[PDB]
Length: 132
Length: 131
Image 1 (cartoon, one colour):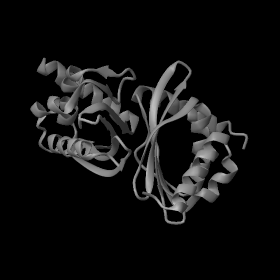
Image 2 (cartoon, one colour):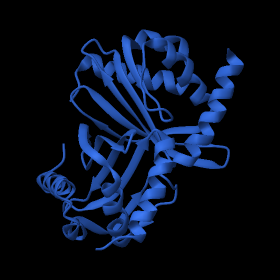
Image 3 (cartoon, chains in turn blue, green):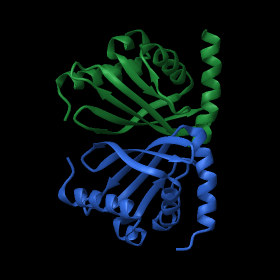
Image 4 (cartoon, chains in turn purple, brown):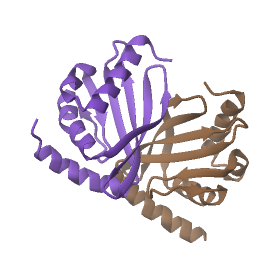
């Protein structure tokens, strides 16, 4: 069962996602955070890639809803449902926190794969079109 | 934290996957088990589809190894690593158990998506071949 700091980090993750409050994302991330995304195998390192990619990914997911959740001593897996137009999907956010309650690892996976292929094209376009 | 029957069910799941002992898997499944696979959205229902698909998938995966794991009152998420030839992937098995220690839901997801597409073509071939 995770400590108070980790639980607080989870609460903040949820708030940032619920409110799309991306300006507060960097303070939640550890400097050395790793990010593994649904469409390419190599991880991204550091806060910058997450600052660029996450808001775009969440911008494409419609009717985003967290579903079943699971915990370890240090982290969580958060299942979710969503759609991109008429393309339905489910996925997980696997999130690891350090003792200070900062995110050290984020892995995102989605299914079915065919929808992830489509979503990743749109995410690329969303990143190119970002206004902040 | 799951109960004793569920913990025992998880142990048997691990054994079956580790040995590829598919003949014992039906005994571990609830009759109305729901299975959500990495390549199409709609879940499958009942033991049959799961017993056709899951063994074929594992026949194509190499060096399958469980990594991080997580739990809820009734289930687990088991992260894994594996490869198909020189194409590496990671994934999760989300597994829910009932109070009898039988699997009611299995969801499998993998990344990256491009590798899953390749995997699904090979799994289809093997299902066909075995049919």
